[PDB]
Image (cartoon, rainbow over all chains, first blue to last red; front, side, top):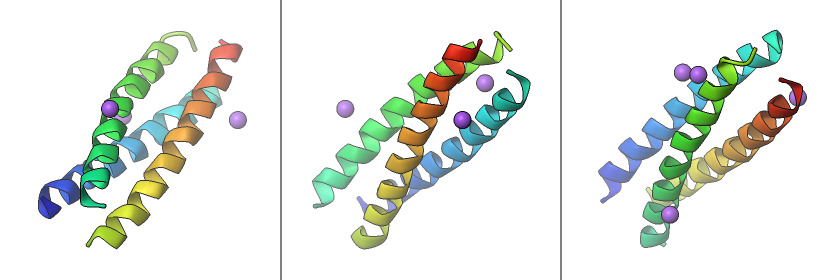
Length: 30
Length: 30
Length: 30
Ligand code: NA
Ligand code: NA
Ligand code: NA
Ligand code: NA
């Protein structure tokens, strides 16, 4: 259970880093 | 405690997809 | 361990809410 949850958390941290970058790009352009 | 963490991770992941789509929709309007 | 996972989930929840705010704002500016 623990290793699967951690791999999911890592996946979340990645998706959120990338979303933050997209948003920061949008904020510059909008 | 453990159950609840796995459920929050599940609802987080089932939210990053909506946010991803919302951001992709915004990328087209700027 | 569960402690670290809870700490990361609280960080991910905060970033989620912040990105949701960022997206609401961007929607008003396009
Ligand atoms: Na991305
Ligand atoms: Na859910
Ligand atoms: Na995008
Ligand atoms: Na802002």
